[PDB]
Every structure is written in C-alpha cells, then in structure tokens.
Length: 35
Length: 35
Length: 49
Ligand SMILES: *[C@@H]1O[C@H](CO)[C@@H](O)[C@H](O)[C@H]1NC(C)=O
Ligand SMILES: *[C@@H]1O[C@H](CO)[C@@H](O)[C@H](O)[C@H]1NC(C)=O
Ligand SMILES: *[C@@H]1O[C@H](CO)[C@@H](O)[C@H](O)[C@H]1NC(C)=O
Image 1: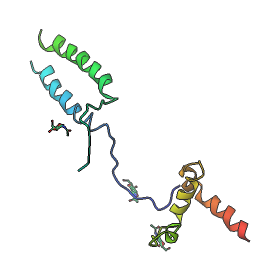
Image 2: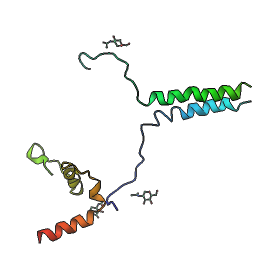
Image 3: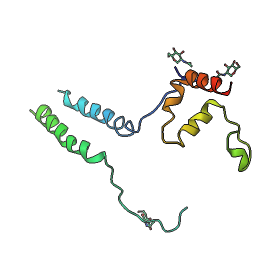
Image 4: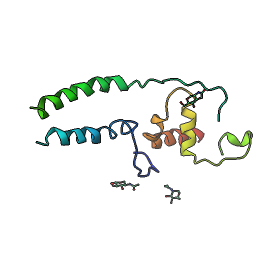
C-alpha cells in the first residue's frame, strides 16, 4: 500500500553475535559428528 | 580524539543468557563425542 | 523545503515525507501515513474546497 518504496537488503544486530557463533557452533558440530 | 575518557568494562545485556547456554551445549558435545 | 529554509540553506524534501516528519512531532508515529495515504489526500482535497 506504500508508494515510492524500493528494494534493499536489511541487517540485524544479531548476526554480529549469531553469524559469528552459528558458524562457530557449526564448527563444533563438525567435531560433534566426526567419529 | 576525546579528552578525559575512562577505561571501563561495558557489559553486554545479551551476553550471559547465551553464555549460560554455552556450557549446556558443551555438555552435549562432551556427552556425545567422547564416548 | 519544509522548515529548514527559515534557519539556513533551503534543503529540498519530497512532500510525502514531510508529513512523516510532522506526524512524528505530535506523538503518533509515521506508520499511520503511508498505509492510508489516499484517504488523507481526499480528506485534504475536500477540505480546501
Ligand atoms: C515522480 O513523478 C513522476 C511524474 O509523474 C513519475 O513519473 C515518477 O514515477 C515519480 N517517482 C516515483 C519514485 O514514483
Ligand atoms: C522487489 O523484489 C520483488 C521480488 O524480489 C519484486 O516482485 C518487486 O517488484 C521488487 N520491487 C522493486 C521496487 O524493485
Ligand atoms: C586504557 O587502556 C589502554 C590500553 O590498555 C592504555 O594504553 C591506556 O593508557 C588506558 N587509559 C586511559 C586511556 O586513560
């Protein structure tokens, strides 16, 4: 319903926490199911 | 570039809630990988 | 230009966002502007006539 809008990506202040740790928890998941 | 600033340790309000889950995840990592 | 031209250089602004900077000075946010922009215009067009 809004006019004049444009498309753009938006960020969240949680990927400086989560996406610095979800890759770290996936790295721990690599060691979790290694044997 | 500022006069008279003071060194201090500013807390993070989202830190200890996930930090309490860190040892809970490490408990699963210890319980699965080691045996 | 809005209100800036009385206090320095004239800064041009589009008029749909000037209402968004004038609802916000009342106490209701700018969320209630673009959601029903057409009926605000019809309430404004019929008022001057
Ligand atoms: C600005 O107005 C012109 C004139 O009608 C129109 O063609 C153009 O689409 C408008 N700009 C936007 C972003 O809608
Ligand atoms: C934004 O993206 C969606 C789908 O990706 C598309 O349908 C829409 O037309 C796009 N809007 C603009 C203004 O580019
Ligand atoms: C704050 O810490 C830095 C680095 O640890 C140190 O160089 C500085 O002398 C400290 N004190 C200040 C800025 O008053």
